[PDB]
Image (cartoon, rainbow, N blue to C red; front, side):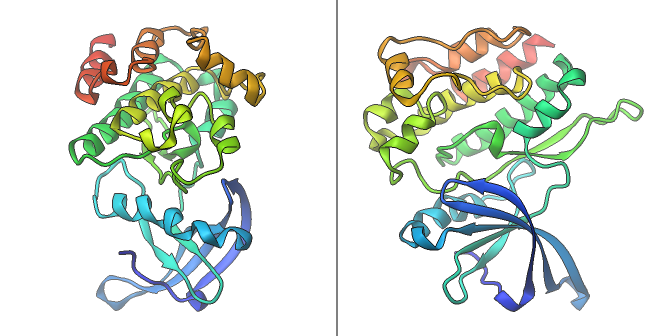
Length: 274
């Protein structure tokens, strides 16, 4: 289980937006670190809405399970603050924010090599999860954090981490799941209890589509009724203008979950493109 952090050691600063039944803030944690040195550490504070306290177990659960598995491409959770009426997840603060925003902001200069590197790193994270039979359940660009930017001057590629999934689609309202088409795969719209490792392969494809589409969100022009019919008609996403990953996107977003390729095979596919 997560380490418990006192409310007194957390300072809330600026809002950084909202998630599903959550509000997100930049903050600071006062802590004693290694060698007993005192630190004033920048943190990301994810706060469950008071009205939705009933989702608290799910809010913390998969995050907790992920945090038991240390990996260079998985987000660092420091712990939780559950003092008083608060349900707060305390995370590392990532300077450059999440990928959905970054892609839009730096659209004019993100190229195939950058995308490929980011795709490979995400696949590495997902393979690690697959090997540990741990379902993520919400792979998307919003849940990818940019730890560091590319530096051509020095040879450094960008570096990302996969963030926590938030509250599970197994407990969310049907209308939220529908809004999340096409990240939520067809079998989970049919029955949320179908959440499986194969789920993450589909969402990974949707996420590659984002990475190639400059901040665009697939099917955003479709209301929830039309998103449902999109799956009923067995449509695929349009190929991004930069189509280098289109085949992979389609191979991952397979309406047959058993046919979706392993992350090992996906990684081998990615390596062949360079």
